[PDB]
Amino acid sequence: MKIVVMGDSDTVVGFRLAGVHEAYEYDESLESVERARNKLRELLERDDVGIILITERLAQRIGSLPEVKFPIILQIPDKFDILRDVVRRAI
Amino acid sequence: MKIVVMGDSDTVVGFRLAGVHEAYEYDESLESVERARNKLRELLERDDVGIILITERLAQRIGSLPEVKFPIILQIPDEDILRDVVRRAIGV
Image (cartoon, rainbow over all chains, first blue to last red; front, side):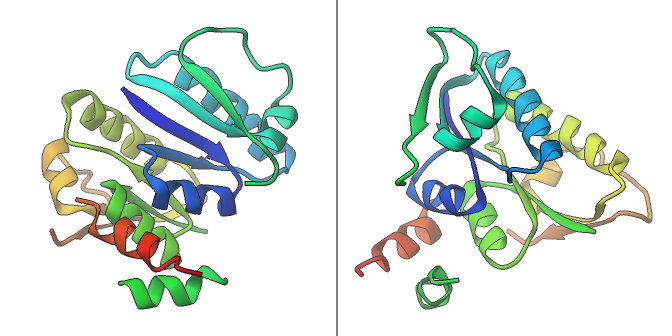
């Protein structure tokens, strides 16, 4: 099963570099939030998704998240072009 | 107008960091490939998507590729070496 992260662009960069299997980026515009809302409903229906990591802000923008025991849903606390030098030097 | 990339994690994180607007990861499992097929079909229907960059592997796994002129579909010539390197680089 897969580990998916949903959040803003910054948070997503880090988590992708850290090992998640799938990532979806969103900003706080109404349209983006609506898309994340539908995305979340979609991930809940996939039998190959076990863990969803979502930023506290996005979770609150979406609203009252579903009450399911599986997949596991974790909220990334609001604490977690500078990486431009790191990127170029790396690759 | 957006440029999208579809492929494995290493490729995806690299292209997103290189400027690509949207990126979607896929492995080679049947279910993941099937999700890629549907995603491709959806991207063709979006008005804000002009370019789709897809790894050579994934495109071949999908099989049939659209024959459209727009959006522009480009294959990327053919693992965690990239994510690992950027991670190690974070010795700040």
